[PDB]
Image: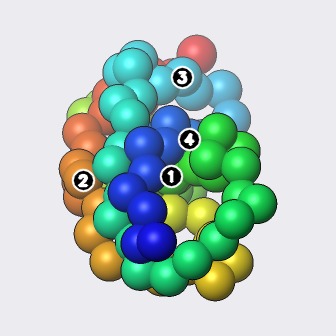
Amino acid sequence: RDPTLTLSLIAKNTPANSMIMTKLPSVRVKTEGYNPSINVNELFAYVDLSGSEPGEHDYEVKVEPIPNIKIVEISPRVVTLQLEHH
């Protein structure tokens, strides 16, 4: 089926006492494989803010593991976000 998915972007490990000022864009993912029972809306792409300081930085977009599916393309691949200390 090699489904093309549209996933919402989620931020992981957002530093405590800090807030993301940027609205996270959606992500388009091309895949290879088959899977009839995997909730698309329950699937997410993510950016890992582990150890980030306030300001504007670029983060690599990644995809949460999906059974029987291999991610072959992710757009956008990188996202620019702004972080502000509380």
Do the CB atoms of the residues marked 3 and 2 lie less than 8 Å apart? Answer: no
Rate crowding at label 3 as few (under 14), some (14 to 19) or many (20 or more) other CA atoms within 10 Å: some
Q: Residue at x 47, y 25 (%)?
A: 20
Q: Earlier in the sequence, mark 1 or mark 3?
A: 3
Q: Residues within 10 Å of mark 1 (few under 14, many from 20)?
A: many
Q: Which residue is mark 1?
A: 45
Q: Which residue is mark 2?
A: 75
**Cα–Cα gap, marks 3 and 2:** 24 Å
Which residue carries the number 3 mark?
Answer: 19
How far apart in space, not on screen, are marks 4 and 3 (Cα)?
13 Å
Q: Earlier in the sequence, mark 3 or mark 2?
A: 3
Q: Is residue 76 visible?
A: yes
Task: Report the side of 39 relative to 50 (left or right).
Answer: right
Q: Quadrant of residue 27?
A: top left
Which type of secondary structure does the marked residue at label 3 adopt?
strand
Amino acid of disc 3: Met
Looking at the image, which residue is at 54% across and 22% down?
A: 19
Counting from the top left corner in percent of width and height, residue 70 is at: 48, 82
> Viewer-proximal residue, 56 or 45?
45
* Label 4: which secondary element: strand
The x and y percentages for residue 84 are 44, 22
Q: Identify the mark nearer the N-term, 4 or 3.
A: 4
Amino acid type shown at disc 2: Ser
Q: Disc 2 or disc 4, which is closer to the eye?
A: 2
Disc 2 is placed on an element classified as strand
Against 50, residue 7 (above or below) is above
- Mark 1 near mark 4, Cβ–Cβ under 8 Å? yes
